[PDB]
Image (cartoon, rainbow, N blue to C red):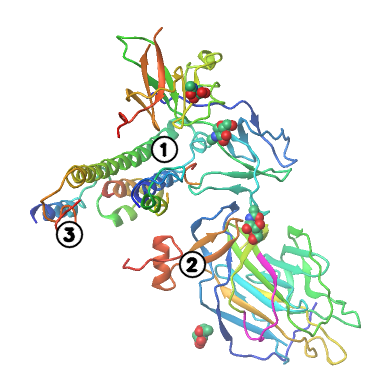
Amino acid sequence: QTSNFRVQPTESIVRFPCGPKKSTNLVKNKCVNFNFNGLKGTGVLTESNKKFLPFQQFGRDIADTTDAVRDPQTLEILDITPCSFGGVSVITPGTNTSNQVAVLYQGVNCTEVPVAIHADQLTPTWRVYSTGSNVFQTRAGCLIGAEYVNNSYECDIPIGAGICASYQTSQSIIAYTMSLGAENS
Amino acid sequence: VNHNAQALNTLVKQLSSKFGAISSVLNDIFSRLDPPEAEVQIDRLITGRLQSLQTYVTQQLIRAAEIRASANLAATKMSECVLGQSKRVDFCGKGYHLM
Amino acid sequence: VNHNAQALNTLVKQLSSKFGAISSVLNDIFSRLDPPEAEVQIDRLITGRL
Amino acid sequence: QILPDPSKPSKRSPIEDLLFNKVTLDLICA
Amino acid sequence: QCVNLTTRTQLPPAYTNSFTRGVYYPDKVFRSSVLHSTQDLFLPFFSNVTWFHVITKRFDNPVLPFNDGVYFASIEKSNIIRGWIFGTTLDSKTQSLLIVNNATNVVIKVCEFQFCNDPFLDHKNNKSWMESEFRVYSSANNCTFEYVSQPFLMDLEGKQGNFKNLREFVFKNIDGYFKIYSKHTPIIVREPEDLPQGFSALEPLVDLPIGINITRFQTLLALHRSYLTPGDSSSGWTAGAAAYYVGYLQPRTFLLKYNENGTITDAVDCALDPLSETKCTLKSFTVEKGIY
Ligand SMILES: *[C@@H]1O[C@H](CO)[C@@H](O)[C@H](O)[C@H]1NC(C)=O
Ligand SMILES: *[C@@H]1O[C@H](CO)[C@@H](O)[C@H](O)[C@H]1NC(C)=O
Ligand SMILES: *[C@@H]1O[C@H](CO)[C@@H](O)[C@H](O)[C@H]1NC(C)=O
Ligand SMILES: *[C@@H]1O[C@H](CO)[C@@H](O)[C@H](O)[C@H]1NC(C)=O
């Protein structure tokens, strides 16, 4: 494990209810920074259908975290889903044998992988064409750098949810659905 | 399932505790004050959240030992009651064990 | 019986420990000080007993 | 009642179906 | 200037019971299908709630103290209960607050008014029962705050029929800051004794930063007079059947059941009886068999 996957805000919206000195815009479906009347945070401002009891301005989940905010002048109910949070997991065959790796992102669709790792100088510049091919979507995230086959072998390196991976055959990393044993009657 | 969901809900509900500091929001600590005197408040919050994480992990280790004792018993019962016939009294049910 | 009684005597003799605070009797902190600068020793005692 | 039932898409026995329905597993997103 | 009103009838107070009433929203927050524990100032469940009635002539205008917030309610048909005064001295020596909810404007005034000691609500009513005189105060020396909110509209007719309105009002003072919560609802005609069993939540309406010291309050009526009402401004009046209910708020913990729409539909008082206290410490609305 190397917990790295943090997607980043593209822009900021400091929308105010047709008032104090300014209002910016409303944005949907993308990873943004929001400050609705002093509510600084990072999220995805997708719309919703929650009846919101007109004096109320905030919404909370089970764990008292800010969930749905009304539009302050358009008066429409918008969810907060903070775009963040994966884990990078690294599949290697051992460095004495090869130096090529495969990378698992633990909980995402990787229609939306390619944006960012960002801490100090770790950076998008690996990623901008290393998405490419060899992208396989599992139920344990999605896996980059390994090629799916229809054979069924013994488990060598356990990815998860019934998927294992190995290194063989112009050698490469393969990923397969693991086999339980020899068939018998 | 109830113990696992209960421990996770306890761990996420302990993020709103101040532990004696003035706030539970980090930007309100970095606004409204100055950093050499906010430094002791964020050390108070970091030490409180670290003790919350450590006391989560300790009960997870104790419960994992309990589940491991139960799983070793289930592996013994599968080897001895399912894959064979047992002579041990009340190990595979009440009465003389058939299968 | 010995380990249970010994753990309970350890728990009741840990109520005499200052844990870096100015006293171990609570009214001594709540008298003779202003409560904004008495709150810190109360937080030290509540943490250390906890 | 213990052998697998080939009609259902999850090839489980009827007893395993009742054991799966009686254990009930959003707070997950929070 | 006013003439002091006389022929008042003194009665012992008739009491009743508050049948799970007076639960508001403490916060500005939508919550969905959760159970939240709020420690605030409420009317306790099954509390000992006062009753006054107005038809000599059954004059109920007491000077009531305002200790820590007041539940006020009225089951009513033709808008007789219209106003409130608040304060300590009420005689142009200290700042006094005034709310008047008439058919024209919701008027809030904070000033050193020289109130009449039992104020005139004269209402020289012909076939249109219109207010012709307003002698509640007389003067204003040096004072700041006045405010008018959005009114809602009343008939101002002398109805003697059936009650259908149930007005509910909550008055609070937090950090020099006056909160008015409300619920106005239609009520069925029933036996005219008390408020029935039921539950409803109370959305906030009027929030105001006055910052004065409030000790007592007193209700401003709207008396109606007619050709069956002979007499002067202090003795001769017949109002018709009206009633109001005064309950007092206490620092209590409640357990609130928010619905999927954000309206709380059920509450649990936490120090009433041990079954509800078990429901508090389990954070549930049903309790499985056992010992806790
Ligand atoms: C992942 O992508 C697929 C393809 O569009 C979609 O059906 C699914 O809902 C997505 N899941 C999440 C959690 O985004
Ligand atoms: C091998 O797997 C791919 C993707 O899972 C599938 O499209 C293809 O048809 C499979 N080949 C055979 C021979 O089944
Ligand atoms: C309210 O309190 C008084 C105490 O003087 C008591 O007589 C009365 O019965 C109480 N009301 C109810 C409904 O119990
Ligand atoms: C709110 O209540 C109404 C009527 O009961 C109904 O539409 C639904 O149950 C609730 N939610 C929404 C979003 O309308």
Q: Nearer the viewer, residue E112 or D6?
A: D6
Q: Secondary structure at mark 3?
A: loop
Q: Chain of mark 3?
A: B
Marks 1 & 3, CB-CB < 8 Å contact: no
Which kind of residue does numbered mark 2 sit on? Val
Q: Secondary structure at mark 2?
A: strand
Task: Provide residue C16's location: percent of width, then percent of height.
Answer: 20, 51
Name which residue lies at 18% across and 55% down. Answer: C12
Tell whether position E186 is magenta.
yes
User: What's drawn in magenta, residue-wise?
Assistant: E182-195
Q: Secondary structure at mark 1?
A: helix
Q: Residue E50's quadrant in the figure?
A: bottom right
First in sequence, mark 1 or 3: give its number.
Answer: 1
Which kind of residue does numbered mark 3 sit on? Lys
The quadrant the N terminus of chain A occupies is top left
Dot label at residue B94: 3
Which kind of residue does numbered mark 1 sit on? Gln
Task: Provide residue A36's location: percent of width, then percent of height.
Answer: 64, 39
Q: Chain of mark 1?
A: B
Q: CA distance from mark 1 to mark 3?
A: 62 Å
Secondary structure predominantly adopted by residues drawn in magenta: loop
Dot 3: within a 10 Å radius of its alpha carbon, few (fewer than 14), some, or many (20 or more) residues?
Answer: few
| Residue labelled with disc 2 | E268
| Residue labelled with disc 1 | B41
Residue extending farthest to the left is C2
